[PDB]
Amino acid sequence: DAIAIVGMSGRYPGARNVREYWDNLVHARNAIRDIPTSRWDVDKYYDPVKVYCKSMGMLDDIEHFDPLFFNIPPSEAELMDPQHRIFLQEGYKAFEDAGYNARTLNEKKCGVYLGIMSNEYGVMLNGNSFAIAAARIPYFLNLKGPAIPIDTACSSSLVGTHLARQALINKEIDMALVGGVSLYLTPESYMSMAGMLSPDGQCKAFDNGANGFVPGEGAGALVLKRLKDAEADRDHIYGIIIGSGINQDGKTNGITAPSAKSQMDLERDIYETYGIHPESISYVEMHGTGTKQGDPIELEALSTVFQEKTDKKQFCAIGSVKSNIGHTSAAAGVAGVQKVLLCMNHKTLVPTLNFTTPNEHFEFEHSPLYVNTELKPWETADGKPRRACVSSFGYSGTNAHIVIEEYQPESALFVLSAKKEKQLKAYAEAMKDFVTSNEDIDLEDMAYTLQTGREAMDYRMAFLADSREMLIKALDDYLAEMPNGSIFAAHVKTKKSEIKLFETDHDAKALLQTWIEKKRLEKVAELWVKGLQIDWNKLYGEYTPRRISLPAYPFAEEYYWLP
Amino acid sequence: DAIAIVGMSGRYPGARNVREYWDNLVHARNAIRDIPTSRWDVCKSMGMLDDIEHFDPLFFNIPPSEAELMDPQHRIFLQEGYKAFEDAGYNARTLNEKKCGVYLGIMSNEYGVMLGNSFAIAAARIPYFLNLKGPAIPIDTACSSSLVGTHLARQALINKEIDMALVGGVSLYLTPESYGANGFVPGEGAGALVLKRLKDAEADRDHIYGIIIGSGINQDGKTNGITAPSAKSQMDLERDIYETYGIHPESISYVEMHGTGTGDPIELEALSTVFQEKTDKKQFCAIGSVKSNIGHTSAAAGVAGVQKVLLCMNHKTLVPTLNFTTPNEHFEFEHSPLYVNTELKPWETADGKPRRACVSSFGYSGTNAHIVIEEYQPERSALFVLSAKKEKQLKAYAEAMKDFVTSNEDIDLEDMAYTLQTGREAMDYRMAFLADSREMLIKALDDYLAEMPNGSIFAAHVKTKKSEIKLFETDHDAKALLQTWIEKKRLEKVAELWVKGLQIDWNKLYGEYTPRRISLPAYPFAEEYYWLP
């Protein structure tokens, strides 16, 4: 039936994570920049009539990787496509976002479906097959569901989402990591213009001045489960997928041209199959690439399908994040889904950019659709959950469309750890920023998540806090190395002797168990940082807190490029 | 009634301790040497102690600079006295505030003059260090000093004025100025005994070397010259003691004579006459003098003799008296109760009667003493612990224990561990180990000394491990775990924790078999040189 999205991680132009992404969207920020010479020299390729676009939605630090975290030799890192490296990181972080760790994922029937469409690094070098790109994560975490790369060009990550959904419903897997990754590493590839690119370097979605897309980079992952399992497992749930479908354009006027009829059929069939009335939908994240013939075809298709069922006018907002971050290709779908989920969570619609005058080839006034250019509350009538769609179409003609529905749910001991001390310090900084930014965080949920939803690694710190202010001060104290009697920190390999007593002796265990049961948190904390395994469940009686989204591991930022 | 001797320590010519002393006596060794030029430039002979300058002032909370200003007589007795307590199995903790008297025989001031150093302070050193509360009295009755002290301590214990007494003597010969039978050769020495009422010693489960069943002191009075002896006074002394305390001369089988080798014939006649008043029996009582081995140890003479007698009783063995070829012309042995023993032989007793002996000590000032001693007749892995105030001394302690165990094939391992646990202060530098046999024990100590890794051996400096044992000191279930460990089996765990500084309740290791304290090697003091500043 319904598929729950229980974890996400995103890395897009101008946004190192989904929290920065959200902030940028709310503030209607455009992340497209001129291509710097550190990538390539546009002047050596630029011709205005060769490349005729000098702009890109770019990721920062595409060379950074933490190979030691993944048990990969540093020298092997140089030989890895950064698309592989970046997804390995984001994919991992999605799991941690959900509150799952290596221990809890071991032997899980989790499928991995990875959108990917380019091979630039591999060619530059003359391990880097699509097949291996997908298999990296399963190999690392010991997952047992199929690992499949999907190259349907720009629809890739949405197509993957469909396949994962069907495998989950058919009970072939019990979890799914779906995502996409796209980088533009060479003048040659980003180049193919074929007439595709805008000379102004913007995706002018829905606008009469639409004249092509600007290439964007991105890497995004989702964690999917059956809704029934997600509720039983007490996951935190971003939203639910209540319908999806994929099809083909077939014979068009040129293989990269779109088909109105196919787009209508896709959308109509989905709504009919899953009993979804177009009136129930209030936002659509369009493919919306800002191409002159593509935009009006998409608009006309969707409008027509909606109008078949309803006379209501201008009830459904449309937008495209490609207006913000460019066309992130294989990662386009996951970028779009993540926008909609964030919109749902905050009950807020955000502006679509670069829209001045409606495309002449489509009339909005008598349409169910309207272009939203406002930061405004996402209103819903009665009790009803918000519903949205995401479309993604590829140049090869393979189309995807999913329907997402809002999910409507019915002193603490803080522990942190990392594989190196430097990353532990980075972790504490990320948590401090997060708590600073999120004034309403549930302290018990957060602590519970750090306890049960993160792997205890070798470098540890812990502390007590009963308030946001106390929490922030503890982290500040830790970071500033200024003495605080409630802060504990150790390297586990150093302390083995100081812990053995509680591991072997019968009365010491019984003491430790009593400590945990009577909530003697200082004592539990001191021992935990030293490496003692704590049964966290014992900390909780009638009331158990819930896992929530927190910042994920802050990987070492080590530079690896061509050998 | 009876007084138990529950601790002893001794340092005599040729003997750094009471075990070497015994060995020397058994082998009829003579410790008299020519006086070297390092003492002074030269009678040219003396019974000398070795390294009289050596002291461990830090152990005793004394500034190293003060040590140079201390009479070495004070310093050496401080050490020997302390070791006597440890021999008995008592430590700083268990002695704190005890009503223990200190009676110290001392009769010279050489160092003070050469240069704090009063007799009054000499006696008070140990009480000050250990916080004892019985009177501290120095006794100068010349060569009878330590035996006079013994008498006074005995009377105080019987009157219940004190509950313990440290009695002792110390004599050094530091200057040329203060310095067959032909006179005596001067000897140096320091000795101490620990005394208790017998009833207390048995209730407290002390180990008991022997019991004092009679003692007396008196004066020569008017003699022909103040340093001459009085046959009559010696007789009266001995008779009065035997009569007061119901002691029949026939029961006595050894007498350690004053026996300075001058005097001799008067002592022989006196004792012989007193014995003969009560018995016709001939040549039943052996006589000797340890002054033939070690010289005339002066203030320490009494304690040296008492220790010889106790060692004899313990080993049920009589040892040779030396330098005897032909009897003194002025006394006829053949029809006497007395005979000079020159043999190493079994000390025989009839029908399981306890052996009895006497010690006589007579001073040049005319103050005499005589005491009567009776032999005392009493009715799995272990955890061995050692500690010292410096690592160097811990190493020396381990060596001393290994030698001791090597020399004593019949040591009770449980008793020894028990003594190391309860009868020594746990100090800052620690080692511990398990053993279930003599061989394992010796091996462990060897391994420790040779620095050969051994999984049964644990060692730590306590100041370094504080953070590591806190986990056990305050928490209730950690204590329960420790109590389960020590209540009871894992010993390895108790050992690891103990060396790190955790206080253990040694009693809990024992359900209703409890082992007994025994004599073991005492602290091996740092051997630092201090002399005139």
Image (cartoon, coloured by chain):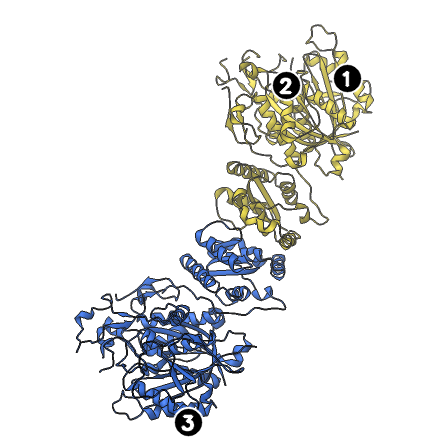
Chain colours: A blue, B yellow
Whether residue A252 is visible to the viewer of this picture, yes or no, is yes
Secondary element at tag 3: loop
Quarter of the image for residue B320 reads top right
Judged left or right of residue A166, residue B31 is right
Q: Mark 3 or mark 2: which is in front?
A: 3
Residue at mark 1 to residue at mark 3: CA–CA distance: 139 Å
CB contact under 8 Å: marks 3 and 2: no
Residue matched to label 2: B119
Check residue A308 in the rendering and tell me which mark sits there, or answer none: 3
Residue matched to label 1: B237
> In the image, are marks 3 and 2 on the same chain?
no
Residue at x 36%, y 73% (from the top left corner): A219
- Residue type, label 1: Leu
Secondary element at tag 2: helix
Dot 3: few (<14), some (14–19), or many (≥20) neighbours within 10 Å? few
- Residue type, label 2: Phe
Dot 2: few (<14), some (14–19), or many (≥20) neighbours within 10 Å? some
The chain containing the residue under callout 3 comes to A
Q: Is residue B251 above or below residue A4?
A: above
Q: Is residue A431 above or below residue B380?
A: below
Residue at x 43%, y 92% (from the top left corner): A311
Q: Position of residue B20 (x, y in %)?
A: 59, 30
> Who is closer to the viewer here, A376 or B370?
A376
Q: Position of residue B256 (x, y in %)?
A: 69, 22
Judged left or right of residue A557, residue A500 is right
The chain containing the residue under callout 1 comes to B
Marks 1 and 2, the one that precedes in the sequence: 2
> Who is closer to the viewer here, A215 or A228?
A215
Quarter of the image for residue B229 reads top right
Q: Residue placed farthest to the top in the image?
A: B224
- Quadrant that contains the C terminus of chain A: bottom left
